[PDB]
Length: 64
Length: 65
DNA sequence: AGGTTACGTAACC
DNA sequence: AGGTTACGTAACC
Image (tube, rainbow over all chains, first blue to last red; front, side, top):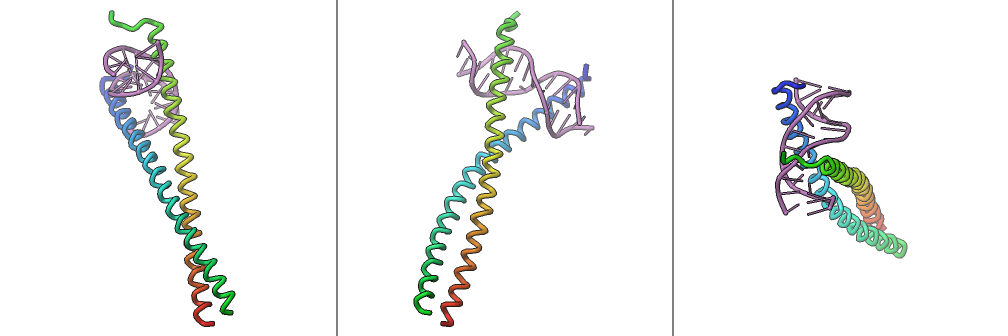
């Protein structure tokens, strides 16, 4: 059977490990919410930029 | 004394095993989703950078003639 | 070395 | 009722 010191170390190592898993879980939950707002905004900017390119392409098609 | 019955011990084990499974299934799903989202962010950002260049190439071409 | 894998214990709600 | 909260145990690498 593990010594009193090894027992104590296993409890502490698990306490720490358990906390890191919780921190990581919460960090991923926030990343999905953030990366979803980030995706919805950069894709809206791409709509405006592709419409801006379609505008300049016909404006060059006309003036040339 | 106050010790749970053999059947209750078995149920606590089963319930914990099932709880752990659900928690891990959600972990793998999030990990996958965050990867799908990160690569999508990197993809639509490269596109945004291509559209910002295509909006300057066409403005230089429509500035000379 | 002790972080990690792996499963358990039991009160609590 | 048993899912959930809360920690522990120890071998493995």
